[PDB]
Image 1 (cartoon, rainbow, N blue to C red):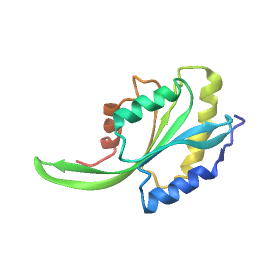
Image 2: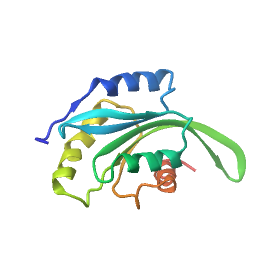
Image 3: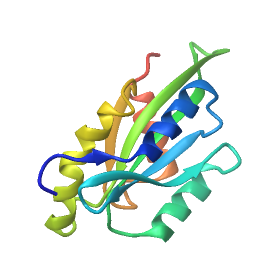
Amino acid sequence: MASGVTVSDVCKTTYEEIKKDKKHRYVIFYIRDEKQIDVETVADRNAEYDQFLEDIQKCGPGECRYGLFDFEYMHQCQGTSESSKKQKLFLMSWCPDTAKVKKKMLYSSSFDALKKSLVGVQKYIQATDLSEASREAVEEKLRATDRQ
């Protein structure tokens, strides 16, 4: 990583689909050649967050990953179960920053780089280790930027 990342076309095609048809519920980005952004994992609502969690950590422990998720979250308030169905896009960087510095240098540039490609996402948050990246930890950061 020499500060300045190239986004692969796989990211564009996924975004153009997820923005219109959104049958690519969440796209997992991987870091390409340690200087480019790539898409090496895609999944839809057929898989749940548990399967998502297990599969990514199975694919690799300590490297850089990203995830753009467009889902309709129903937020209810005041004990009134109106359930405000709000579709929200979130970007999450799955990368152990606490690991090898050569690895965290890579996502350092690309974290802001892909924001240009998947522009329109609401919140971008990083999750380092499996302790920080869990299904519950995912719902916490998505509601933290919401409104009661």
